[PDB]
Image (cartoon, rainbow over all chains, first blue to last red; front, top):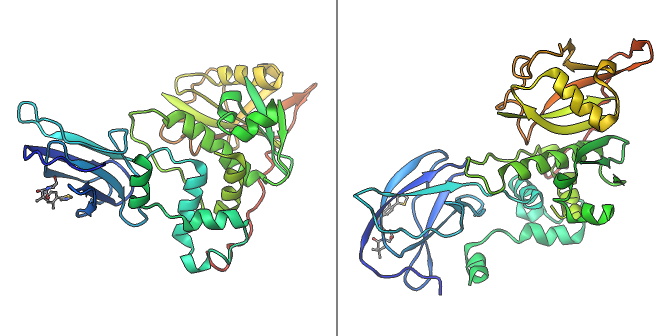
Length: 141
Length: 86
Length: 103
Ligand SMILES: Cc1cc(CNC(=O)[C@@H]2C[C@@H](O)CN2C(=O)CC(C)(C)C)ccc1-c1cncs1
């Protein structure tokens, strides 16, 4: 369902990373498979060649935390008007406090030691349930 | 309009009602003071700071900064956020 | 430009915002509405410094980029009990435990 259209109509795009994270851009190819591309450091940008109707989403390259692009999940390059590239503003969402706490705990404790932490059983499963591109694609679909 | 959120160690935090209603748990606890017996003040102060942060940056075009959390308070803050559903 | 504050006395802590251009006296009017004590029975402090009513919060060092939503600036508060003002006193928050072995 979520797949790039094979339009063959070039569309130049500026990936603008306005987040403090290292960004992993992911191209959903014609069979709907996530295809990773080279990372962007925090605050940097790149001019990239894509195509009209192609699907892109963006993540934290280390933890796969979800990021927004122009205030949304998905970015689809549009027609270029007067030779101007499309701007893809990559930003942090407003994470829930809970998820933000899970992010920080994950980043300090190695997966092996989640069960060693002194917390209720249900938070153990919340920690192990890492952000994942395949999982989100099943949600969106 | 304001409400009082009281930590386990007696600290009384006064925040706006609409900020506090971010938490569905607090909405229920109100329906104008709320005593939290498991949340110490160093956690509850951070919870209040988050409310201000969420209300400010939700549906905002201005670049959003990371919400900071110290390593020392993360576990306790996780437990509170989980309970408060925020 | 909005600034974000914690107005703190004893074990009380008010979370609110104000304009950088607003006055110390106007902040006292906000406190009055919440804690039911008029401006003349209040002293506001930045750290150990007493704040003048007619000065703006910007002049007193509360700026939008330092007094942030996620990390608000502290403004000391002291009440006048009858004739004389109490000394400024802010109870500190609780201390977090030691970082567990795994963190
Ligand atoms: C290294 C790099 C190369 C390219 C080349 N362009 C592509 O691969 C485009 C992007 C996407 O629309 C698919 N694509 C294609 O040329 C079609 C295809 C992969 C040959 C089937 C585009 C972006 C990047 C990036 C550079 N930094 C972050 S992404």
